[PDB]
Image (cartoon, rainbow, N blue to C red; front, side):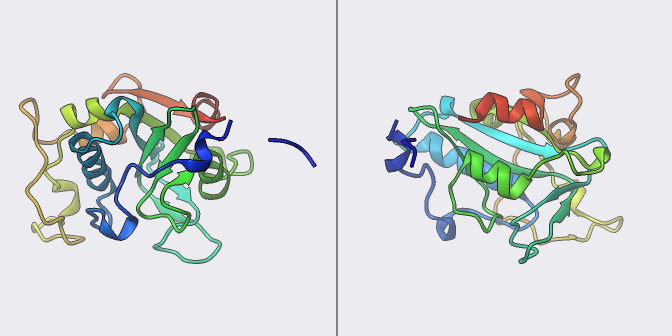
Length: 202
């Protein structure tokens, strides 16, 4: 037996329940943007405690386990995936992934251990990198005209979300600057898996 603060024990979620969140399959950057907007407009938590997290790598092929699109024990291989990270007042981080079969929200260590898993056994070019943008910066700077979701004749590869494209005064499309794991582009900070866990893990 071993005695393991209790703040995380009573943690109240920052989002509506999973079924009530704005959600479109294969638009996780927008699903997370909408979670950020919800948190901003409600009175429960400050945006300063939350981050948008882009997961990808140079070849844009990342395995993620415990994903809804592939029930079972195998991974989905995404080009990129986006989740929301909340650093709660006591220090415990929580991950909000609308596409995970893990709990929504999920304790950080469980998401890293069960959804991401160790990179040690993975061929290095499939390893995961993390771009962490404070949610306020994400809402201020993110823009997507959804042009990456259309084939050469303009047809939608996956049905679009049911609201107009997210744009800013500075840009109508900079999604690649978030998917990139090059620190020379975009906003926020780029972390290896070990740096990500060191920064946000217990």
